[PDB]
Amino acid sequence: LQEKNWSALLTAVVIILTIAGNILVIMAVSLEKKLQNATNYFLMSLAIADMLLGFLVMPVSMLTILYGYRWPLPSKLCAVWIYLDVLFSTASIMHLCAISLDRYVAIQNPIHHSRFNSRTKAFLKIIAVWTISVGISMPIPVFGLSKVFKEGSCLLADDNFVLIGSFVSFFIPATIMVITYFLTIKSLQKEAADLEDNWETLNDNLKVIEKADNAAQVKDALTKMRAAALDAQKATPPKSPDSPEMKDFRHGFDILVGQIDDALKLAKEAQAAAEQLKTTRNAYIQKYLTMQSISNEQKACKVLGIVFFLFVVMWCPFFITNIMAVICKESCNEDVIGALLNVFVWIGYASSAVNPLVYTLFNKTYRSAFSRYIQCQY
Ligand SMILES: CC(C)CCC[C@@H](C)[C@H]1CC[C@H]2[C@@H]3CC=C4C[C@@H](O)CC[C@]4(C)[C@H]3CC[C@]12C
Ligand SMILES: CSc1ccc2c(c1)[C@@H](N1CCN(C)CC1)Cc1ccccc1S2
Ligand SMILES: CCCCCCCC/C=C/CCCCCCCC(=O)O
């Protein structure tokens, strides 16, 4: 028991890293313009929930710890610490889960030429996240004042409250989160195979068109280039600020190939010289922007997979032991599994710390903001 005084300190480390880790994330997304992605707009709100969870309900989880788990505050405010903790936590899965199916639908749909709002779509999307988040949390204060106390410690004790609340707030979202996620990674991976194929196709026939000695050999070789070029025009990862240029440079590049074709049938010696995408800056940019754009979404999917994965890995101990309380009400000792719950809620409460760490470990631009922000300099 000499080493059990460390829990206070170790848990305070989990309280510190979450309040600081997500304070920067709120800062760094707002200040540095290079991180204004729609998916970085979600991350800025999520990180607020983790800031609000660290700032409100993780500490009194420790305050209770010090007292021996006998609830140390007024009787009357227990449903509000359960409510708050339920609400912010339930907003962190909703933020994660929204992100995954927001990115999922966009990859399996086209541009769709909507852009009704000017990247307030994030702002609309996030307020829907919280009202669904606070949709679910009204039942705790609705039956706020019993079903919230057990032997002088404060836990959700209504069996259906803690049974329904697992599927509605944890397993449905975690499953939804993961099911969409994997479909997308398989989808993105299977769309990079199309752009690379379309540029390889385009370059090989370009060499063929130049090196072909027959008169109409160009025809098959430069009609195919038109074919791939359109497919590329139809392909971009989810990511009108740079969408004209892609379309214009698609159109602008197509002109060069199109024109050579137009005068290819007419003819001959000159059209080989006419299809010279090798000599023009336009074509070189487009291969660049796509391969840089393809690779960026690779790393976003991986960084997101890390936060997705270790969110549900970390809270599953607390939810499996808790759902097992009600399923195993009679068979198994409740003083052991109640002990596991004192612990497995800090495996879970520690995810609020983790995701700022994984941002620095894999996003160069998130790293530089934090490092400066520690030094105070914008
Ligand atoms: C109770 C004691 C130990 C402090 C608890 C941790 C928090 C509240 C402390 C510790 C380190 C502090 C931060 C140090 C660095 C920055 C970045 C700066 O650009 C804005 C202020 C800010 C964000 C400070 C605000 C408060 C802070 C986050
Ligand atoms: C009791 S059954 C249940 C159902 C829903 C939710 C919780 C618990 C919540 N706990 C946290 C501990 N706190 C002492 C009580 C409330 C935990 C959590 C974790 C992750 C996302 C959402 C939620 S909301
Ligand atoms: C996705 C990763 C999943 C990891 C699962 C870890 C499981 C943690 C605990 C499981 C429930 C244990 C409950 C122990 C109660 C013992 C019952 C008794 O005393 O009779």
Image (tube, helix red, strand yellow):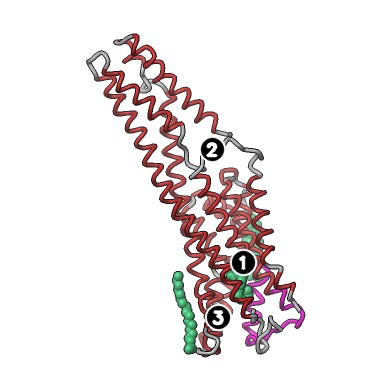
Give, as a single range, the part of the protein colored magenta. 55-81
Q: Main secondary structure of the magenta part?
A: helix
Q: Which mark is residue 274?
A: none
Asked if residue 79 is among those painted magenta in the image, a careful observer would answer yes
The alpha-carbon separation of the residues under discs 2 and 3 comes to 46 Å
Residue 195 picture quarter: top left
**Measured along the vertical axis of the image, is residue 46 above or below residue 109?**
below
Q: Amino acid at mark 1?
A: Ser
Q: Amino acid at mark 3?
A: Leu
Quarter of the image where ligand 1 sits: bottom right
Please report whichever mark, 3 or 1, sits nearer to the chain's N-terminal start.
Answer: 1
What residue is shown with label 2? 111
Asked if residue 76 is among those painted magenta in the image, a careful observer would answer yes
Q: Is residue 15 visible?
A: no
Query: Which residue extends farthest left?
Result: 213
Badge 3 element: helix
What residue is shown with label 3? 341
The answer as to whether callout 1 falls within 8 Å of ligand 2 is: yes
In the rendering, at what x and y percent does residue 104 appear? 51, 50
Foreground residue among 71 and 243? 243
Q: Amino acid at mark 2?
A: Ile
Residue 371 picture quarter: bottom right
- Left or right side of 73 for 125: left
- Please tell me which residue is depicted at 55% across the width and 75% down the height of the picture: 346
